[PDB]
Amino acid sequence: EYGYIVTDQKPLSLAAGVKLLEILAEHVHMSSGSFINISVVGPALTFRIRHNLSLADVTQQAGLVKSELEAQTGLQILQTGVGQ
Amino acid sequence: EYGYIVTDQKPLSLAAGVKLLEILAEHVHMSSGSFINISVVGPALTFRIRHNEQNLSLADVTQQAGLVKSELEAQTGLQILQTGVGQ
Ligand SMILES: [Ca+2]
Image (cartoon, rainbow over the protein chains, first blue to last red):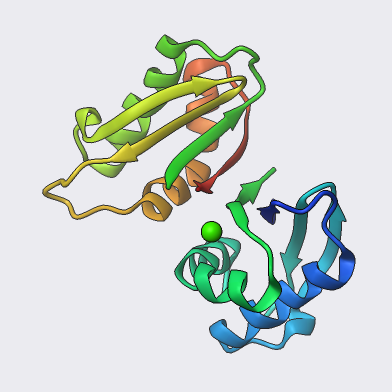
């Protein structure tokens, strides 16, 4: 399983994807280095989480703070979820 | 915003989509009629959730759909590839 965030960026930069994860990490009180196996592919950011909070927790939290994520990164978040 | 379930069936049938919802509803102890504004688009099912006695959320029901993906797959033959919330 992996977490993902689909943005409006065509394509999403690696720098902006990591910025999303830094902000997300802060909101869940985890080190951003606990986001592992990160990739950007087209508009999407994908990631897993290291031993430390679950993917469910973090994608739920990404919804909770979506406004803040969008304002700080200058992009729009179109989907957040879990894949496998 | 909408909840969604992405399958490996393109086009996904409406009837199969709502069978997914019936299994999910049984698992979360909600009436399936509390899934509203339903559509199928490509391989995906999209929906919202009505006021319900259980006070359940989108992340809540889409999290659950991911947990019971083996059961959704066993019962319907679909493969569940993604679950999430969209805008
Ligand atoms: Ca937005």
